[PDB]
Image (cartoon, grey):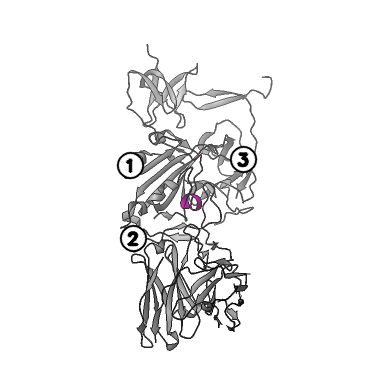
């Protein structure tokens, strides 16, 4: 059901915002003054446009100096109640030179949301460049 | 098809490689006048956006699409700002745009009540009052339809022949560059001491084959001292260890 | 600033007449040429006019659909043709000129010169 | 169109006397009124333009005034040669014309 997100600030469907969503078999990424449904349902001026439980899709998103950074990783699940624990690192997929601010977002139809902050980590690398572990340097005295 | 000058067209060019070698070295252009930029350095420039202004005017009107100009075209059809950055390119289109009976499908604004601001277009059909009596929207004595068609004919002298004029307007610092010219590469030379530049990663050293396996994302690596260990080539993804020159 | 008109003609009702006036060279770059008719025993009536610098023509309502006004820029000659003539169309057809400002297109309402007039009998 | 009326249709004066002609339009033309003097055998001669401006070659005895819809021609003193038919012209129409005898 979740096919994407809308990111932006005002998000009033009158100004431009960033829409990342599945469109048939391709994903469309665009920034436009699109008249969005206030709460869209997916059944059965522009800056740019680009066109490309069961398992978990993890993502991390940040917006730096106008560049929207998209990262992800997929992992199999045999759970029916909550998120799995364990360690993996997400890989970057997309880097979008848009020039807009993001303060709010909407999910396009279990979903979980956390927030990022400037923590320091000690990262353990494998022989092949993989991040295999990490220490959250602000978590406790050890 | 180019727009008439009053019906000015504007194409937005973004997220691409701005190869201008096709334009500044073109012998088909009679005019290639760059403002703030050098024609042969256009490939070294980056823009947030490039806008392409595409229209048809007479030969003696070519000079009007420029910063600092005034006149019926410069003031009523299209104005460029006095501090305009970009290039005004023009060529004769007598064999494309002129028609034997006159290519009157092209029009320019002859009448307006004010001058245009930079990058302003005016496609209004409001009847202009030239005289003292009201027109009330109707053509008549000292009341005119604002547009004047062009008698572009194959037999016109050069100043009256049509020209296809394109202005490439350069937008900077509103958003990150999305339009940049091409980057020229060299051959890849192995087992020699060289001065290298892989995209934006530079240094001096000897390039030899690496036994490293980079994650698909990783393009280059780092040693324990955070010096470059190896660099994967930008065209063929081979990883080359960089040995310091002895 | 002279204007020489063609001489008199006699037409069968239902036929057309093409009346022409020759202006001094250079007239077309600074003047418009209007047509005025005078039926014998009557006053003046305006029929229409051409502006050579705009390629525009304006007509009297009673002649819309009946009169075509044009000009030949290479011969400095104004033309008017009435498509279908009736006996009430007997008149002296005059050409007369109004100066026009080529930058603003403000036309004068008065004639600073009239030709002698062309009499067409129907 | 603009309907124009001239008045009186005819005037009767001796040479040496003052005469005026009135013209009225159904529509305003601001100042765009031309006055012409026509004699038999001649195309009308412009006397006055833009309601009150004397035409080149026309003597000082001719003057006038008016605006909008209401205009007047004045001949301060008629000469034996002024017993002509006068016409009021606007950009689109003419009045019937007035005879001075």
User: Which mark is in front, 1 or 3?
Assistant: 1
**Residue nearest the observer in this picture, B41 or C10:** C10
**SS for tag 3?**
loop
Q: Which mark is residue A53?
A: none
**Residue at the spot of label 2:** B99
Considering only vertical position in the picture, is D74 above or below B50? below
Subunit of mark 1?
Answer: B
The picture places residue C65, in percent across and down from the top left corner, at: 45, 79
Q: Residue beneath label 1, please?
A: B26
- Residue numbers of the magenta segment: B69-83
Q: Is residue B34 above or below residue B78?
A: above
Q: Is residue D25 visible?
A: no
Rendering quarter of residue B128: bottom right
Outermost front residue: D16
Whether labels 1 and 2 belong to a single chain: the reply is yes
State the residue position of label 3. A102
Q: Are marks 1 and 2 in contact (CB under 8 Å)?
A: no
Q: Residue at x 34, y 59 (%)?
A: B153
* Magenta-drawn stretch, dominant element (helix, strand or loop): loop
Q: Is residue A56 above or below residue A123?
A: below
Gap in angstroms between the C-alphas marked 1 and 2: 26 Å
Distance of label 3 from label 2 (alpha carbons): 54 Å
Q: Nearer the viewer, residue D32 or B118?
A: D32
Q: Residue at x 53, y 77 (%)?
A: D82
- Residue B76 in magenta stretch: yes
Q: Which chain letter goes with mark 3?
A: A
- Using the numbered discs, state the Cα–Cα distance from disc 1 to disc 3 in whole angstroms: 44 Å
Q: Residues within 10 Å of mark 1 (few under 14, many from 20)?
A: few
Quarter holding the N terminus of chain B is bottom left
């Amino acid at each position: 059901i979740i096919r994407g997100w809308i990111f932006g600030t005002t998000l009033d469907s009158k100004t431009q915002s960033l829409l990342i969503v599945n469109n048939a078999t391709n994903v469309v990424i665009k920034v436009c003054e699109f008249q969005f449904c206030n709460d869209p349902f997916l059944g059965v001026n522009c800056t740019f446009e680009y066109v490309s439980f069961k398992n978990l899709r993890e993502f991390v998103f940040k917006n730096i100096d106008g560049y929207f950074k998209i990262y992800s990783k997929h992992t199999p699940i045999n759970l029916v109640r909550d998120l799995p624990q364990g360690f993996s690192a997400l890989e970057p997929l997309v880097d979008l030179p848009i020039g807009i601010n993001i303060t709010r977002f909407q999910t396009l139809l279990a979903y979980y949301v956390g927030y990022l902050q400037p923590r320091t980590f000690l990262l353990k690398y494998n022989e092949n460049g993989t991040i295999t572990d990490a220490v959250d340097c602000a978590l406790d005295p050890l | 098809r180019f727009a008439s000058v009053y019906a000015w067209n504007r194409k937005r060019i973004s997220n691409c490689v701005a190869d201008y070698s096709v334009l500044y070295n073109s012998a088909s252009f009679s005019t290639f006048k760059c403002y703030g930029v050098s024609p042969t350095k256009l490939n070294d420039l980056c823009f947030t956006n490039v806008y392409a202004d595409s229209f048809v005017i007479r030969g003696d009107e070519v000079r009007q699409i420029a910063p600092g100009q005034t006149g019926k075209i410069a003031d009523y059809n299209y104005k460029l700002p006095d501090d305009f950055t970009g290039c005004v390119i023009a060529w004769n289109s007598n064999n494309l745009d002129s028609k034997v009976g006159g290519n009157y499908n092209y029009l320019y604004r002859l009448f307006r009540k004010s001058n245009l601001k930079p990058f302003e277009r005016d496609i209004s059909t409001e009847i202009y009052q030239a005289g003292s009596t009201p027109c009330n929207g109707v053509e008549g004595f000292n009341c005119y339809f604002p547009l004047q068609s062009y008698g572009f004919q194959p037999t016109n002298g050069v100043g009256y022949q049509p020209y296809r004029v394109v202005v490439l307007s350069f937008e900077l610092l509103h958003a990150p560059a999305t339009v940049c010219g091409p980057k020229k590469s060299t051959n890849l030379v192995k087992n020699k001491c060289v001065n290298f530049n892989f995209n934006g990663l530079t240094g001096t050293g000897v390039l030899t084959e690496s036994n490293k396996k980079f994650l698909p994302f990783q393009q280059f690596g780092r040693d324990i001292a955070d010096t470059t260990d190896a660099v994967r080539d930008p065209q063929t993804l081979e990883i080359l260890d960089i040995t310091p020159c002895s | 600033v002279q204007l020489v008109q063609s001489g008199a003609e006699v037409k069968k009702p239902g036929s057309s007449v093409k009346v022409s006036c020759k202006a001094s060279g250079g007239t077309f770059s600074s003047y418009t040429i209007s047509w005025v008719r005078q039926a014998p025993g009557q006053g003046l009536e305006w029929m229409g006019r051409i502006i050579p610098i705009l390629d525009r023509v304006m007509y009297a309502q009673k002649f819309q659909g009946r009169v075509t006004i044009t000009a030949d820029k290479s011969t400095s000659t104004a033309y008017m043709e009435l498509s279908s003539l009736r006996s009430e169309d007997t008149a002296v057809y005059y050409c007369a000129r109004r100066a026009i400002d080529s930058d603003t297109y403000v036309e004068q309402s008065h004639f600073d010169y009239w030709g002698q007039g062309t009499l067409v009998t129907v | 169109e603009i309907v124009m009326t001239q008045s009186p249709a005819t005037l009767s004066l001796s040479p040496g006397e003052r005469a005026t002609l009135s013209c009225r339009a159904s529509q305003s033309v601001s100042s765009y009124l031309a006055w012409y003097q026509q004699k038999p055998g001649q195309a009308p001669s412009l006397l006055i333009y833009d309601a009150s401006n004397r035409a080149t070659g026309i003597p000082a005895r001719f003057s006038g005034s008016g605006s909008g819809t209401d205009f007047t021609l004045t001949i301060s003193s008629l000469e034996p040669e002024d017993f002509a038919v006068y016409y009021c012209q606007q950009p689109l129409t003419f009045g019937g014309g007035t005879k001075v005898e």
